[PDB]
Image (tube, coloured by chain):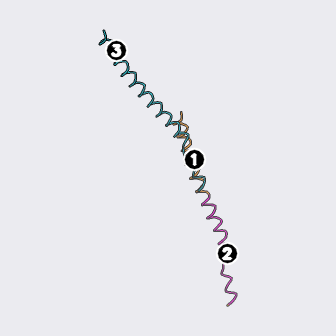
Chain colours: A orange, B cyan
Amino acid sequence: RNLAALEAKISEAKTKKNMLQARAKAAKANAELQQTLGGLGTSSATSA
Amino acid sequence: RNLAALEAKISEAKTKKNMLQARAKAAKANAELQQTLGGLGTSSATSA
């Protein structure tokens, strides 16, 4: 029974951590994309 | 008669001590297994 419980714990922890990390990476990538969209610097030609 | 008694004593002492040692070793192994089941350290990923 301890082995069954430990296997369940290991599987759930591994899969949940992996998916959480993947989703956090996707979210930060999306935030970076939004920043770049707002961070466009082509307006510097106003100096010329 | 002394030889018969001594042989009985020797046989019983040897077998009883051997079985007691084996069972104590099995019990300590089981306790170690339970400790390891309770001693899982995979939770340290909470830091990451």
**Could you say whether the residue bearing mark 2 is in a helix, strand or loop?**
loop
Residue B26 appears left or right of B8: right
B6 or A36, which lies in front?
B6
Please determine whether, in this image, residue A41 is positioned above or below residue B45. Answer: below
Residue at numbered disc 1: A13
What is the spatial separation of the Cα atoms under label 3 and label 2, in whole angstroms?
A: 94 Å
**Dividing the image into 4 quarters, which one contains the C terminus of chain A?**
bottom right
N-terminal of the two: label 2 or label 1?
Answer: 1
**Could you say whether the residue bearing mark 1 is in a helix, strand or loop?**
helix
Disc 1 marks a residue whose amino acid type is Ala
* Of the two numbered discs 3 and 1 in the rendering, the one whose residue sits closer to the viewer: 3
Residue at numbered disc 2: A39
- Residue B1: in magenta span: no
Residue B31 appears left or right of A30: left
Disc 2 marks a residue whose amino acid type is Gly
Please determine whether, in this image, residue B24 is positioned above or below residue B1. Answer: below
- Measured as percent of width and height from the top left, residue A26 is found at 61, 60
Residue at numbered disc 3: B8
Which residue is painted at 61% across and 57% down in the image?
Answer: A23
Q: Disc 2 is attached to a residue of which chain?
A: A
* Of the two numbered discs 2 and 1 in the rendering, the one whose residue sits closer to the viewer: 1
A41 or A9, which lies in front?
A9
Q: Which residues are magenta?
A: A24-47
Q: Residue furthest bottom?
A: A48
- Measured as percent of width and height from the top left, residue B17 is found at 40, 24
